[PDB]
Image (cartoon, rainbow over all chains, first blue to last red; front, side, top):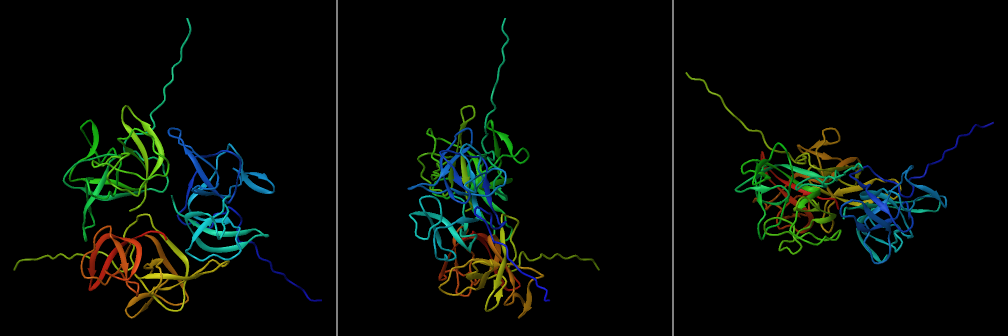
Amino acid sequence: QINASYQRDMAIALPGMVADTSKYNIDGACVVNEGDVLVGAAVQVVQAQAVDGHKLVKALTTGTTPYGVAIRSHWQTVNAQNQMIYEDGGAINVMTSGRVWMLSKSTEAPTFGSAVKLDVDGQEKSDGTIETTWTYAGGWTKYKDIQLVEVQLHQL
Amino acid sequence: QINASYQRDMAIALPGMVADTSKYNIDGACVVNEGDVLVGAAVQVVQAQAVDGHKLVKALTTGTTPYGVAIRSHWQTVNAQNQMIYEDGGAINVMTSGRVWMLSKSTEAPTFGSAVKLDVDGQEKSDGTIETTWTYAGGWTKYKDIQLVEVQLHQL
Amino acid sequence: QINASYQRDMAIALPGMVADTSKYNIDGACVVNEGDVLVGAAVQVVQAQAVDGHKLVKALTTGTTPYGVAIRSHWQTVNAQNQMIYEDGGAINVMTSGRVWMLSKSTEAPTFGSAVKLDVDGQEKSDGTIETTWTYAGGWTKYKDIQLVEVQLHQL
C-alpha cells in the first residue's frame, strides 16, 4: 500500500475581528438603543450624556455620520440567528481607530488608499450613499460565503 | 422623633483635568515665555528652537492658531490669583491630543462632534474669532460657578 | 607650563533616526520591491496583497503619494556606498506616524507648522512638486555635511 498525508488551510478572519495590533482605540462607555447591532457594522451616535458620560449609539441609518465599528468579544454578545450580536440595553465595544474586518456587500476588490463608502445599513458597499473618512487597507477574503474587507479607521 | 440621613454627590471635574485615559499625548519640553498661563487655557507657540529643542509657549492671543492645552500638576504649577497657574520661565506641560476639561464662557450646551471656537484670551466660546480643528466630546458640567467643557484635541 | 582641558559637543541626530518617544507607529510587514531604498527617505506602496497581507513598497517617484519614512535598524539593513540601505526583496521598517529626522535638500530653516513639500526622489525640499499632509516639527541641524530636518508624520 501507499501511505498518504493531507493538507488543509484555516480561514483568515471572521466578521468584527480586529485585524492588527497597531495603535487602536476602543470606547467602552457606550450603550445601545432601539434594537440590535450586528458585530462588524457601523454605528451612529444619537446623544452624549452631559453629566453621566455614556454615549448612546444605534445601527447606522440614512443621512447620518458613522462613528465606529463594533468588535468581537466572547462575553458581551448574545447568540441569535447563528451569529453574535449586541442586544438592546447592554454595553458595547466600539473601535474608533485602528484596523478592523468589516462585512461587505460589494463584488470587486477595493483599491488601497481609496475612501470607503457605506450602505444605509452599515455594511460596506463599493458604491454607497454615505461618505466617510475611513480608508481601505487592502485585505480581501471570504469565510464560508461571507464577504470581508479590511478597513482603517481614523478618530472623528 | 424620626432619624434622618443625608447624601451628597462629588463634583465631576476641575479645570485642566484629564477626562479619559484614551490615547493622549503630553509635551513636557515646552517653556513659558513672557507671561502667565492658567491651567485649562489654550497656548500658542512663539518660536521652536532648531538645536536646543525647547519650544517657547505663551498665552493665546488674536490672529494665531493654538497648539495645546495646559493641564494640572501638583509639583510643576504655582498658586496665584486664587488659582493654579504656570509661572514664567518654567517648564510647562501641554497636552496635544486626547480629552481635556477646559474653561468656557458659553451658556448653551454644545453638540457632539461640532467644531470648537476659541476666544481671544484662550477660553472656549460659542462665538469665537479663532478657527480650530479640535472637537467637542459632550461633557458639560459646572463646579461652583465655573463653566467647564470636554474638548477632544487632535495632534497638530 | 600650564595645563589645559578641552570640550566638544556631539551631533544632534542621524538620518532616519526617531526624533523622540512621542506616540509613534511602525510597519514591519512591508517588503521592498524592484530596487533599493535609502534610509531617511520617503517610500510609496505599489500593491497590497489581498490574502497574504504583505505590502510591496519602493522608492518615491513623480505622480505618486507618499506612505511613510524608513528608519535606522542595525540588524535589518546593509552597508552600501558608505551608507545604510534596505536591499531589494527584504523586510523594511516604515514609520507611519511620529517625529523623524530625514534628509533634506533645502538651504534655509523651515517654518514650524508648515506643510511639507517633497522632491521626486523622496527627500524633503522647499518649493517641491509633491504635496503631502505632514508638517515640520522644528528641527534644523547638519551632521558632518548632511542636511537633516524634523518631520511630523500622520497616518494616511
